[PDB]
Image: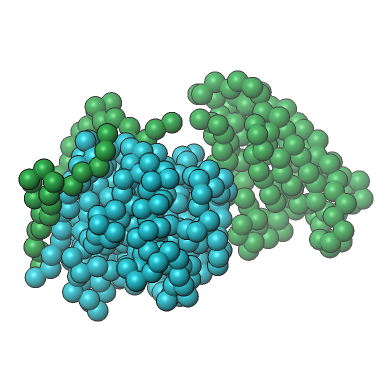
Chain colours: A green, B cyan
Amino acid sequence: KRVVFADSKGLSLTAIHVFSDLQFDLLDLNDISSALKHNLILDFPQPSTDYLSFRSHFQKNFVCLENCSLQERTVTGTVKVKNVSFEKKVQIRITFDSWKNYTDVDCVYMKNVYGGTDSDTFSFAIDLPPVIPTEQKIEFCISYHANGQVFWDNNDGQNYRIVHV
Amino acid sequence: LNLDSIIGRLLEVQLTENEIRGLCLKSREIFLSQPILLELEAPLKICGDIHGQYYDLLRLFEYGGFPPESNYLFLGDYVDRGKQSLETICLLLAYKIKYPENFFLLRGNHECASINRIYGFYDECKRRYNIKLWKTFTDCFNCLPIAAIVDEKIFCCHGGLSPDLQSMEQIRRIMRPTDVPDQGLLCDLLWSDPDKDVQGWGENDRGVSFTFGAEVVAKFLHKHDLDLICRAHQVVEDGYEFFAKRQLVTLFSAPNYCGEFDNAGAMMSVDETLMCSFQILKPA
Ligand SMILES: OC[C@H]1O[C@@H]2O[C@H]3[C@H](O)[C@@H](O)[C@@H](O[C@H]4[C@H](O)[C@@H](O)[C@@H](O[C@H]5[C@H](O)[C@@H](O)[C@@H](O[C@H]6[C@H](O)[C@@H](O)[C@@H](O[C@H]7[C@H](O)[C@@H](O)[C@@H](O[C@H]8[C@H](O)[C@@H](O)[C@@H](O[C@H]1[C@H](O)[C@H]2O)O[C@@H]8CO)O[C@@H]7CO)O[C@@H]6CO)O[C@@H]5CO)O[C@@H]4CO)O[C@@H]3CO
């Protein structure tokens, strides 16, 4: 297959229209075929991309997801927490089956020399299962235990979602 | 999010800020799920800059067929200078969400924050909605793909070639989301121009990127076994313009460009056999 212009085979090259109500149809989408030739992705922008709303969530809930990347089929990230006591427990609560089950991954303290003495930041890394059926949902949220209380980042009630293939 | 209520409202000529936010998030996830160097299968209609001239985009669809009656590929520059960037980009993202494998959007040099802050889009967002919406649009734009190869024969991008581009794997390695730098491969693909009076590469009068002559185009095509460069970044009077003996073509789909000009708009229709023709909007 190879490019050829309409001039070359006798037809008009150009077709010019001079210028100066809605109608509805129903369509079977299998009768049109894909124009594209041919993994996992995050279904949310990193909360930290918009600092003002990240600050708003972080100061309202005392915990907020800071950064999150999907490295291979492993999800890795950083969580920010308000430094209310000395001992803390930061957990990622994640599901690979639309919340029929979940598991609690423990997060890790990061030295983080700069970042103030008002917040601390924790890391996490979670290996996704090798095979996940396509109809299942992958979602996760964040718990922060400190000072006799529990705090949650649940992304304003939608959870952080990850979508497949 | 109800896509069909939105497309319905847009095609009657007002949208809530959350509908627009929704279009941005959903389209962003789609853009990331598909390659950054799209590999497309003709038949195909390829269009140049729209620059917010929404009624002229609607005319483009009236003439070339509303989606998915025809497949489209857009070479960037959706949102500046004109009077209706918001409507233009919302119809395009709505259609990308509705027919994600038959509607394609490439990134042009005006889908960058450093540019559309200055030439009008930010002002439209600020007046009609608020700044946060423009920040969301910017994160969306950072995920647009950069170039397309139709049927292993036509190479499409918004600006043109780059003196760094030895193989396509460079383009495929570019990570998203990303801003456009002031120099380098991604910059050149959105900013560089052909010039008839240049042997090889030279400086670019806009102060960004470079300029390439016909010999750069022919050597490129032969190295990659390609047939036609298809780009779209500068007004041309007839709507389309040939270069290097029909080895490159410039498309520009916004007629009477912000009233300063008197140019026609054009769009290239390529059928299954890779036979190309042009469809033009000449104003009165
Ligand atoms: O286990 C299946 C469960 O999974 C999904 O929910 C998950 C959710 O998406 C995650 O975010 C996670 O993490 C926590 C949550 O996000 C935090 O916000 C916090 O929740 C606080 C609430 O926000 C706050 O409103 C309050 O909640 C109280 C309610 O007001 C009150 O109604 C009552 O709750 C009882 C309900 O009456 C009743 O519905 C019943 O709950 C069942 C659900 O209806 C059913 O759908 C399913 O839940 C799913 C859910 O749909 C998914 O989205 O099973 C449930 C069985 O319990 O029973 C409730 C009481 O037992 O009382 C609550 C407080 O108890 O306070 C809470 C904090 O106290 O905490 C969440 C973790 O506890 O949560 C789940 C994953 O565990």
Q: Nearer the viewer, residue A74 or B11?
A: A74
Q: Nearer the viewer, residue B151 or B103?
A: B151
In the image, residue A3 sits, relative to residue B200, either above or below, namely: above
Asked where in the image residue B275 lies, by quadrant, the reply is top left
Left or right: A87 in relation to B31: right
Report the residue at 25% width, 47% height from top. B45
Left or right: A122 in relation to A1: right
Does residue B48 appear in this view?
Answer: no
In the image, residue B235 sits, relative to residue A107, either above or below, namely: below
Report the residue at 24% width, 27% height from top. A31
Please state the horizontal and vertical placement of residue B190, each as a whole percent of the image. Answer: 44, 60
Q: Residue furthest right?
A: A86
Left or right: B217 in relation to A33: right
Please state the horizontal and vertical placement of residue B152, each as a whole percent of the image. Answer: 36, 38
Quarter holding the N terminus of chain B is top left
Does residue B168 appear in this view?
Answer: yes
Left or right: B125 in relation to A89: left
Quarter holding the C terminus of chain B is bottom left
Please state the horizontal and vertical placement of residue B160, each as a whole percent of the image. Answer: 40, 58
Report the residue at 30% width, 71% height from top. B83
Report the residue at 18% width, 74% height from top. B262
Total marks drawn? 0
Please state the horizontal and vertical placement of residue B25, each as a whole percent of the image. Answer: 48, 48
Q: Nearer the viewer, residue A38 or B50?
A: A38
